[PDB]
Length: 257
Ligand SMILES: O=C1NS(=O)(=O)c2ccccc21
Ligand SMILES: O=C1NS(=O)(=O)c2ccccc21
Ligand SMILES: [Zn+2]
Image 1 (cartoon, rainbow, N blue to C red):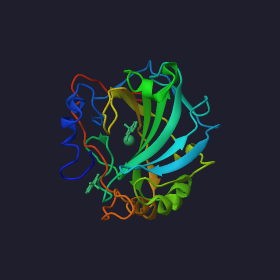
Image 2 (cartoon, rainbow, N blue to C red):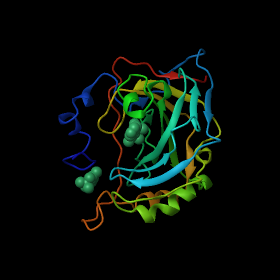
Image 3 (cartoon, rainbow, N blue to C red):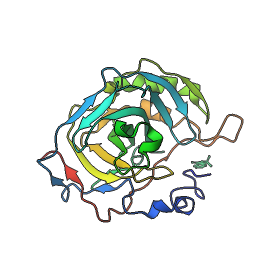
Image 4 (cartoon, helix red, strand yellow):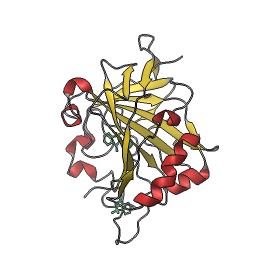
């Protein structure tokens, strides 16, 4: 089964998932000097006021906070997107050290972690159908650097002890994901893929330029999670990131000058 270890990590994934070597794989390095300002891009619309979080789960490769997506409650619109995308879950990728952990890079710079807010296109009815479409998902990517604490993250970090190992979940209601956003919604966008198997090429990526700051204590608690299940040898959940993939025939567009 796939993971981030030495003989099941990203360099192995193509054997079970040939699309790993495909034409629009993610993440990528964002070369800021080559990204072109696109004046026809619209401002992002992030409408999270009615979000209903449900559960938090350790799935053995990250932890995810899940939302009620049976209605238009928390949606992403505008920007590069046509139509309405419902928030399904968010999760993170992070490192064993502050100098690595993000999946996207900016002029080859790696951040300590990366937040992915995953949304699916409501015209396809459910997320399973959406992942089979080239415009099925929109993922909002946000970089984390280590410095001052992010108050809106603390509720997440404080429940992680209760989902230490693979397969554990806990109630996680009334969490407001607006507390995870930076001030600016300036972004880069490009067509790409899931960054975990099955690596489906169904994602419009929207990566925010402004990172959020989190404290060393907050990210250290990420690194106390386990890849393994309860009663198995402990393997810390760290470095659960896929490295940058070939850009190939794609252009990254910027929403800002
Ligand atoms: O992602 C992973 N699954 S695993 O528990 O086999 C493991 C061990 C070491 C490093 C990473 C990983
Ligand atoms: O681990 C993931 N990174 S991602 O935002 O591309 C994504 C989308 C859907 C399911 C999982 C994942
Ligand atoms: Zn992700």
